[PDB]
Image 1 (tube, helix red, strand yellow):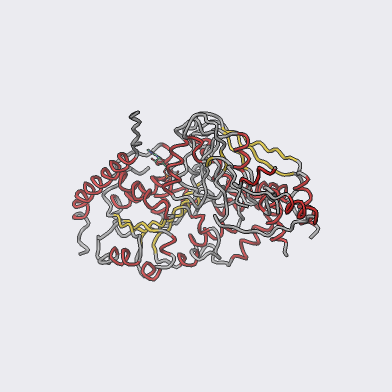
Image 2 (image 1 turned 90 degrees about the vertical axis):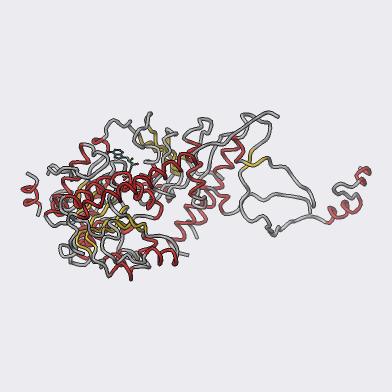
Length: 43
Length: 65
Length: 307
Length: 126
Ligand SMILES: Nc1ncnc2c1ncn2[C@@H]1O[C@H](COP(=O)(O)OP(=O)(O)O)[C@@H](O)[C@H]1O
């Protein structure tokens, strides 16, 4: 407590990677959601 | 009266087909079930001729005409 | 303040950021971080599209990296944009622990479980529809930087948000809005007093004695149209940064505003004359607006059918 | 009634109101800015002000302008976005010598008030 001047600036890497992964998953979800799903097969 | 008219297909489906013979009218507003008072002014001869020469919907009595 | 800031601004480094700022965004970041370093609150009045959100994100990143200002940061943005600000913070600076405080009573209760712990979160994102009634939990907090997106919701001091957010304990305050005016000059006072109370400590009357003369400059009443406007500019100079997109991104096409006016149809003429020769001025204006749009708004033509 | 009028003339459109769900709003935006067939995009003036991106259109017709400004601007900015490929023509309809004339005048006055107030060179230079 009150002693993370540098420990915080070092541990920030893990949170950065975590949020990166989370936001990449968000973008992937949005991309897959943007699809059209149209199929006119002319029976 | 029982008369049902055809104002046309819904307006949102205008983009469905390229060109069609159907007419497009905006989604009717207001509640599906609505009433209203009409202050009509007619004559007695109208009722006389309506009861002497009846009319109606989907009745074969129209053959009288 | 203006002179000593010009002296201070006679350039920082965008450290700890994924993307890169544009030449003008870097200058805005420099201006507002120098403002911070000088212990002054300001308004980033950059027009829409210029990307003040990324500028504020880079400012927070710089504060956390260089000044070690990792403490809790509160960002109040409209509910429809909370997701946008969260995505922006994650794409540009994922290092910050982001606390997206939203949901129902139980969800928010759960999300506040253990938030008093140090370093549990670095940037808190919420909305006015939420902080307005949960101020009891946020008021008693040591916020370092208070950020409000789309500050136009705080346009007036009679709206329960200006009051709810006024006494929020915070070290620094930042307002993001593209239109601080065009409703009245009192909105500028509502925004500034929230920003610098001791500077505008005088109640709304003081800036009303600034607007009323200024408003007459547009109307028939006394039309100085000079001197007082330059004094107002001097007063607003050290607080707000304003830039127009026509020159920052001038590559945009030109836009033309055309105004055409038509006559009123008899069906419109009769109704307008009837309402004019009639309630209250507000009700009359509303009925006239309703008439000018279309007369069917009152009663469409009656469908006729036999009796 | 605007749709009732546009139908009589045969003009494709995709209305947008506050009652529409944000999902439906985004879907209509994406379908309009992509499909070239739709000619009109009827919407309210003071609807969702942020997130709107209707670069697919190239002209604006303000039917019922508001007394106060900054919202017609937010409305104009829905088509006058960054990346626009063609010039935007904004048409404003006013029914003569009515309350509408007054609203237009007041809007202009407010715009002048705001222009003379904030557009006085508040850049990082000075
Ligand atoms: N320097 C930049 N690099 C990449 N994208 C940018 C940059 N500046 C702005 N943008 C884009 O501009 C958009 C507008 O973001 P935001 O600032 O939230 O909107 P507003 O302009 O209304 O403030 C964002 O989606 C962002 O991707």
